[PDB]
Length: 431
Ligand SMILES: OC[C@H]1O[C@@H](O[C@H]2[C@H](O)[C@@H](O)[C@H](O)O[C@@H]2CO)[C@H](O)[C@@H](O)[C@H]1O
Ligand SMILES: *[C@@H]1O[C@H](CO)[C@@H](O)[C@H](O)[C@H]1NC(C)=O
Image 1 (cartoon, rainbow, N blue to C red):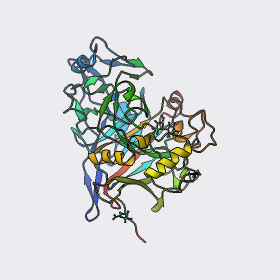
Image 2: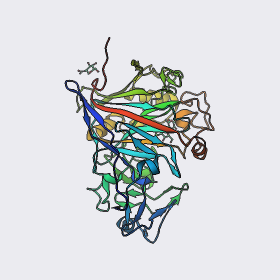
Image 3: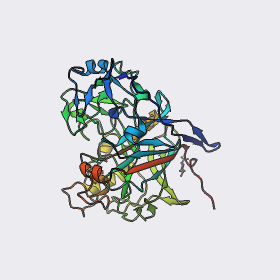
Image 4: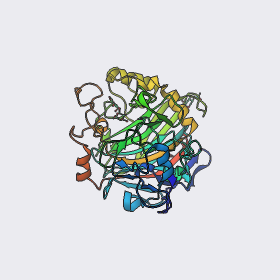
């Protein structure tokens, strides 16, 4: 895609802090940028759309290369069109804004590069307010193995780059992404909703879901892929789990893991109020070259340090962190295939973290599964009493997009106080 000039692109500021044991925390002047899928795409020589609703203009876009040559991504009215605002340290993502639904942004080092986070033997910490983020919604904060320039160096057809939010990939190998590898994904374009469709290619990479949650339920989930970095897929390489990527991941949701009273409204982690979420990526030798061996989680709310809940499922050791053994055990216990191990488990996830990953923040609803995998019973054909089926208390009828979009359109998530750095250094304690 080309870089459009009809609307200035001004990235909202969202300061983060980088911390060390000896020196404490220092601010970085990071920014956020809207993902390319949400933007206006129009002819390079004017105002005519290349894409309207859920279809491409086959005149401007008869094939992927012609389309990318003819078509520019343009700047965004962050608040007015997308419901995205920042105070400078706190990011508010609103659900529905006019006819727009949801958003995804990436953390930027400067106006043309994503911030590349290398989090092996490091931790990532943030605050979240989910008080207005109900059943059926997901306020997500996560890492993808995107290129820092959004693919510009690799793909001559992409002249827009990170400044316009290009180059997305994730462990679901999504085929609804409009530009991949510098070409519009127009082959066999198939409508999937009023504003969305899929093409013949998907875009795959390893993904670490630090946080997917709403005020009912939360999960953290590594998803390794056998590939290294953003990879375009076709055919069965794109296929969930059996292809390049572990689509299911190895997840830790406290409720799914057998503690129904740890996290939620008025619970130990009280989701009716803001709280702090720490995630630590430990290596086997406590160096940045070691093998990722454990992902730990600590919460802090009202100044109380709250350790993660313990697993309480027959056949699963009662642990409170993600490890390769926990993953094997829960997968066996829940009857799920360990695609995670097949793709290389924590070691493969860790090599992606070591190479550097891009931070995404998003608010979304779920056309595929109604977010039931997060906050309800899932899959919908299994006995809710079987180990693993129940993930929250939201009704099994909840989360259909047309419903939440009309019922709770002013839902929002607020992400703030973003920090990363040495383990134990982004927060402190005392007696
Ligand atoms: O596809 C929806 C959702 O799947 C989660 O993976 C599931 C899964 O689909 C399932 O069959 C199983 O038993 O539990 C999983 C974990 O909730 C993914 O983690 C999520 O990213 C979505 O992709
Ligand atoms: C690595 O650090 C952990 C503390 O998180 C400690 O328990 C362990 O002994 C350390 N291991 C090595 C090899 O230093």
